[PDB]
Image (tube, rainbow, N blue to C red):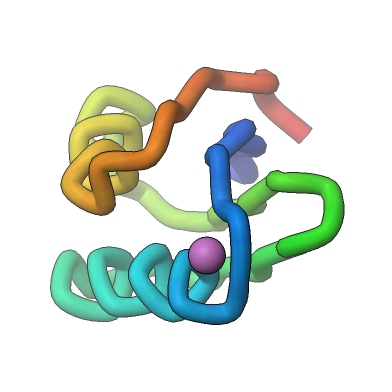
Length: 67
Ligand SMILES: [Pt+2]
């Protein structure tokens, strides 16, 4: 599935932090829209796992649904 999340990223370091947690999880194809504070993730990970992984950045995260 393709999941979209709102992630409260402020700058390049925030976008990097998101990338780092997703890279460590593995099994994800993602793209990060820093200006609009959004992250789209295609994977067979559960929405739950993806939410928890994004939250490891410490940024506020919410779920914008399936794409
Ligand atoms: Pt930042």
